[PDB]
Each structure stands twice: as C-alpha cells, then as structure tokens.
Length: 212
Ligand code: HEM
Image (cartoon, rainbow, N blue to C red; front, top):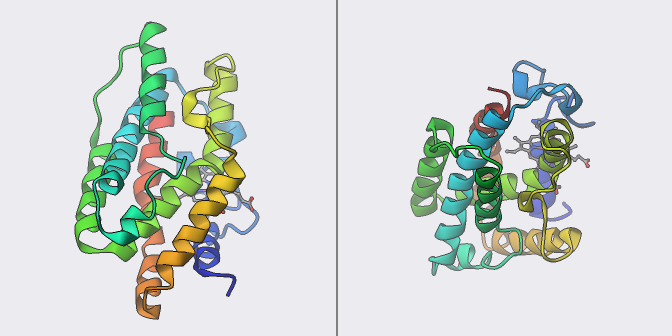
C-alpha cells in the first residue's frame, strides 16, 4: 500500500534466507545461501561471475537503450547501468595477469530469458529489472566487499561505484517503477510479483559461480 515497489520489495525479502536478511523465510540449502562472511571466493570463480554478470547487464541495458516502448524507455540513463563498469573491471583483471573467461550457461541462459520476456511479457521483465539492479546495490555490495577483502586486497572495482549518489539514484528508479505500475492492471501487477522467484533462481545460479 506504500506503492508497488514496496510490494516488490516485500516479496523479494521473503525469498532471502534468514542467513541473509531479517525478513527472509528461505532455508539455507545451497552454497551461495551461506552467510557472506563464510564465503570462500576465488579469483577464477569471481571472474566467471563478472563475465556472466556482464552479459546480463549488457542485455538489460541494450534492451532499454534501444527501446521505444514507454515502459522500458522510462529507465534509460538511471545511473545504475553496469556494463561499462564491468568492462573496466574485466580490463583491470587482464592487466593483473588473469585470463578473462567466456560467458557460461548461467549468464547465457539468463540473458536469453530476459530478451524473450522483453519482447513478450513486460510485467515479468520489469520484475527482473528491479531484482537484478536492486539486489546488486543491497547484498551485492556486501558480497563485493567480502570478495575484495579476501582475494583482491581491497581493490574497489567500478562495478561497486556509482557516478551519482546511490540512495537518490535508487529512489528515482523506485518512483519510475511506481509510475509504470500505475498503468498496469492489478493482475499485471500480480504477474510481476509472481515472477520474483524466477529472478532469484536465475541470479542465484550466477552468484554460485563466485564459489565454483
Ligand atoms: C548472497 C546473496 C544475498 C545476500 C547476502 C542478500 C542480502 C540482502 C540484504 C542484507 C538486503 C537489505 C535488507 C534490509 O536492508 O532490510 C537485501 C535487499 C534486497 N535483495 Fe538481497 N541478498 C542476496 C541475494 C539476492 C538475490 C539473488 C536477489 C534477487 C535476484 C536479491 C534481491 C534483493 C532486493 C530486491 C532487495 C531490496 C533492495 C532495496 O530495497 O533497495 N537479493 N539483500
């Protein structure tokens, strides 16, 4: 009742583990659901995660920049875009001497699924849009810090930097999400919310690469 973004957040928080957040109701079943403080990332797995994340963000950001669909065009130039930052960070790993892997199935499958939804199901597409970006600025930063401390000697990658002030950029996007949702039917809103589990499933398989 605080606007549709609060409904999306309520549904998403319920899908965390208690090992992740106060409101979480999921059991800790997989290795990527362990408390971040207990994670043991490797640079090799982290690179696979960054490459597979880059494909997903490339897909999201290209869909939005090239679209004339007013729902999608509302989210051009949010300040949250990550594709170029990830390119810079993949460049930094190359100069440190690491070889950059090719995108694997978790990134390819998610990127492919997002294109299909962008063409056919805007309500579902928006749900993934919200969960991918707003996860990254929430638990994603906790993961990035833990990875930086343990294996990167506190390098702060561009992936975890924003050109404006993060909290205002997020609230601007929240307002735009509420704006597009007010032109949806209640069922369409409901379809968006029911999509959240799929977003955790696809994102969860990418996060797992950090630990593989
Ligand atoms: C290791 C994995 C994860 C951890 C440790 C984590 C942790 C957190 C934490 C601590 C918060 C903030 C809770 C609060 O301040 O009340 C949060 C918010 C959130 N998380 Fe996660 N999370 C993880 C994975 C995910 C995934 C896979 C998704 C979705 C694909 C997701 C979606 C969200 C969303 C949408 C929010 C709301 C952020 C906002 O309101 O701006 N999280 N998460």
